[PDB]
Image (spheres, coloured by chain):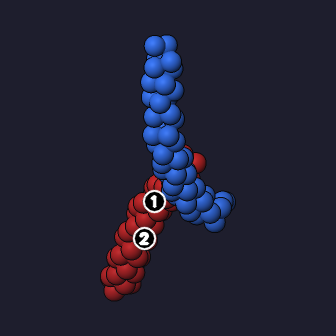
Amino acid sequence: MDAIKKKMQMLKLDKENALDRAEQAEADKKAAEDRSKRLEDELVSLQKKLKATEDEL
Amino acid sequence: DKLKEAETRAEFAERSVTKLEKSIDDLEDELYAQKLKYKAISEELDHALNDMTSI
C-alpha cells in the first residue's frame, strides 16, 4: 500500500541515526583511550626520570 | 404482407434478448469473482498494518 511504505521509511531513518551516533561514539571512545594510554606511558617515563634524578642525588 | 413483416420482426426480436441474458449473467459472475479476489487481497495487508499500527 502507501502508509506501509511510510512506516518502512521511518523504521530505517532512525536506524541510520543510530548508526551515525554509534560511529561517532566509537571514534570518540577510541581517541580518548589512545590519549589515556599515551598519558600512561608519560607517567611511566616521568617515574623513570624521577628514579634517575634520585640516583644522581 | 405486412403480416409477414410482423412475424419476421417478432421472431428475430426474441433472438437478441435470450443470447444477451447468458452474457449478462456471465459478466455478473466474473465481476463478483474479481471483487471477491480484491476483497481477499484487501483485508490481508490491512490486518498486517493493523498489527504494524504503531509497531
Is there any visible trace of residue A28 in the rendered image? Answer: no
Circle on res. A19:
1
Spatial distance from mark 2 to mark 1, Cα to Cα?
21 Å
| Percent of width and height locating residue A10 | 55, 52
Residue toward you, B7 or B17: B7
Q: Residues within 10 Å of mark 1 (few under 14, many from 20)?
A: few
Mark 2 vs mark 1: in front = 1
Q: Residue at x 45, y 28 (%)?
A: B12
**Residue displayed at 52% across by 47% down:** B25
The label shown at residue A33 is: 2
Residue that extends furthest to the top in the rendered view of this protein? B2
Give the camera-side residue of A36 and A43. Answer: A36
Determine the secondary structure under disc 2.
helix
> Which chain can be seen in red?
A
- Marks counted in the figure total 2
Chain letter, blue in picture: B
At 62% across and 63% down in the image, what residue appears? B47
Q: Position of residue B45 (x, y in %)?
A: 55, 59
